[PDB]
Image (cartoon, coloured by chain):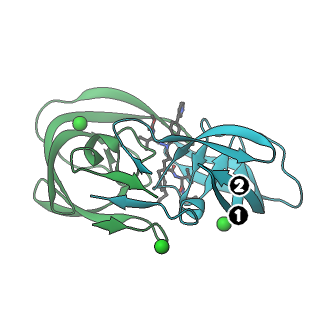
Chain colours: A green, B cyan
Amino acid sequence: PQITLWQRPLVTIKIGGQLKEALLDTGADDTVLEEMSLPGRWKPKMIGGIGGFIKVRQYDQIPIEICGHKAIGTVLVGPTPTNVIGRNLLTQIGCTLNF
Amino acid sequence: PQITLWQRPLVTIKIGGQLKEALLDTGADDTVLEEMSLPGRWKPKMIGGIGGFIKVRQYDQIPIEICGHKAIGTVLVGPTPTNVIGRNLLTQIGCTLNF
Ligand SMILES: C=CCNC(=O)[C@@H](NC(=O)[C@@](O)(CCCN(Cc1ccc(-c2ccncc2)cc1)NC(=O)[C@@H](NC(=O)OC)C(C)(C)C)Cc1ccc(CC=C)cc1)C(C)C
Ligand SMILES: [Cl-]
Ligand SMILES: [Cl-]
Ligand SMILES: [Cl-]
């Protein structure tokens, strides 16, 4: 579709069979989600936002639907003010910026 | 143009006489720039991202130029770790997400 930016670009995603709201964020390298359960082992990452650094859990090869578009990729879980979908999955679902 | 999301979407802006690089961020409510001088009135503001909040100065009705597109809008100045263009100005130059 085509999403204008007069509001927050909030969409519905599906991960682990549950629906969630998340924010499509082109200023983000990475995709980071609020606390939740995911299968398998995880690795550490430090990621930096506008406000400083947080520690998150990295899970790889995780299926996720963004707006009904299927992707499988890396998901971080951590203390974030919102769910955000960063470039790493935006490119999987064929996103570009246009003006 | 059409801008890809394989890489960070960085662009040049002219503002306040200076050239600057900055990051087209669809997730950002506001536009925030590193420390710099702007004319006229301002008020203090706390803004929130990953890792918490920072204090900025808010100037309104500032002329900016982005990729040759003139807009006018609110610009926050402060100790952000990188320059970001937010939805408040992205709208004015007709920028949308597409997939
Ligand atoms: C007051 C209104 C609500 N807050 C906001 O709208 C703020 N927006 C952001 O922080 C956001 O759009 C992220 C900005 C882009 N940022 C840009 C950015 C990039 C690098 C940093 C570098 C950065 C930090 N430290 C050292 C080097 C800092 C910010 N990227 C990241 O922070 C990402 N980090 C990276 O991509 O790092 C590569 C990531 C999400 C994964 C932490 C994500 C975001 C979006 C909305 C909200 C509020 C919603 C409840 C919070 C966070 C500011 C920027 C306006
Ligand atoms: Cl990925
Ligand atoms: Cl504005
Ligand atoms: Cl429009």
Q: Is residue A75 left or right of residue B45?
A: left
User: In front here: A56 or A89?
Assistant: A89
Q: Is mark 1 within 8 Å of ligand 3?
A: yes
Q: Are marks 2 and 1 in contact (CB under 8 Å)?
A: yes
User: In front here: A72 or A35?
Assistant: A72
Eyeballing the image, is A88 above or below B95?
Answer: above
| CA neighbours of label 2 inside 10 A, class few (<14), some (14 to 19), many (20+) | some
Asked if labels 2 and 1 share a chain, the reply is: yes
Q: Residue at coordinates 21% horizontally, 30% vertically from top-left?
A: A42
Q: Chain of mark 1?
A: B
- Which of the labelled discs sits on residue A12, or is there none? none
Q: Position of residue B17 (x, y in %)?
A: 81, 44
- Inspect the image, locate mark 1, and give the three-letter code of the amino acid beneath it: Ile
- Which of the labelled discs sits on residue B72, or is there none? 1
Classify mark 1: helix, strand or loop.
strand
Q: Is residue A2 left or right of residue B81?
A: left
| CA neighbours of label 1 inside 10 A, class few (<14), some (14 to 19), many (20+) | some
Q: Residue at coordinates 11% horizontally, 34% vertically from top-left?
A: A40
Q: Chain of mark 2?
A: B
Where on the picture, by quarter, is residue B20?
top right
- Inspect the image, locate mark 2, and give the three-letter code of the amino acid beneath it: Ile
Q: Position of residue A41 (x, y in %)?
A: 15, 30
Classify mark 2: helix, strand or loop.
strand
Q: Position of residue A6 (x, y in %)?
A: 49, 71
Eyeballing the image, is A44 above or below A3?
Answer: above
Point out the quarter of the image occupied by ligand 3. Answer: bottom right
**Of pointers 2 and 1, the one earlier in the residue sequence:** 2
Q: Position of residue B87 (x, y in %)?
A: 53, 61
Labels in figure, total = 2
Q: Residue at coordinates 33% horizontally, 67% vertically from top-left?
A: A2
Q: Residue at coordinates 62% horizontally, 51% vertically from top-left?
A: B68
Question: Circle 2 sits on which residue?
Answer: B64
